[PDB]
Structures are given as C-alpha cells and as structure tokens.
Length: 50
Length: 137
Image (tube, rainbow over all chains, first blue to last red):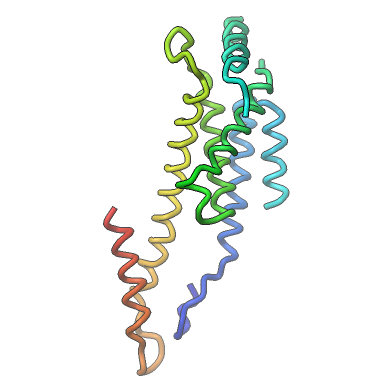
C-alpha cells in the first residue's frame, strides 16, 4: 500500500502478478497429473490471457 | 447440459481401462461444462469476473483429481459428485482470497503517523470495521 498520506492506493500490479503466477503453477500441477489435453489447452489459454 | 447417463458410461469405461496412460476427454469436456454452468449459480456469479476465473480453475483441477475415485454400485450419479466437489473447491478459494485482502486491510490500519497533523476519522473506522467483520469468521 502506498500509504503516503490521504486516501490509500492499491498498487494493483501484484494482483495480476499474483493471479498470473497462480495460473503458472496450476499449469504445471495439471501437467503433473497427465490431464486431458483439452483442459490443458484451456489452462494454456488462461496463462496466455493472464 | 449433458446426459448424466453417458457420463456414467464413459467413467465406467475409464475405470475398466485403469484396471489395465490417459482418459477420454468427453467426460473432461463435460466437466468443464458443468463447472462453468454452476459458476452461473445464484450465490456465486455475483461479484468479480477476475476471481471467478481462478475459482473455476480451482474447481476444475479438483474435479480432475477427484474423478480418480467414484464408485458406481453406490452413488449411481457422477453429476452431483463433481457438482459438490467443485462447490467445495470454490468456497476454499474464496475464503483464501477474502482473508488475504483482509490481511491487507489489517496491515493498513496500523499506520497513522505519516507526516504532520490533520488526520482523518471517517474512513479509518470503515477499514477497521471490515477488518473486524472478516476477522469475526
């Protein structure tokens, strides 16, 4: 949080980062399960959009 | 959406094959389908697209792993199985995120010593009151 007086901002970058990193691990994890490739495609798509 | 019966069929079949590696995707497409359809349920589908994406991600992986074990002789339906599976996955994800941003609020309210005089009273009480409400749980 900036906290530099006044109302406080959210510096939302991390959030994307957060969710971004999230999907990454998911991808691996699901690859780690030998997932049905249709849904691995889906997760690749999620990562790309992220 | 999709005939529950044919899903019973496909899963019986992957059972039989796992009695021998992969599984068919018919059932997997249907899983995506049912997850996304539940997403449009009424308690959810209420707040935030961005969250909802990750929610459904959670639920999908949960159903994926949890398909491993599904009796047929009992629980003659896989539909509701996956349904409640994803349901729980969702609530898990959402509680995590809620208390995360709660943590953010908590960190915030512990900093009023910025520069000089002339503080505010109105807002701070509200960050406080939320940071309390969430903490109630």
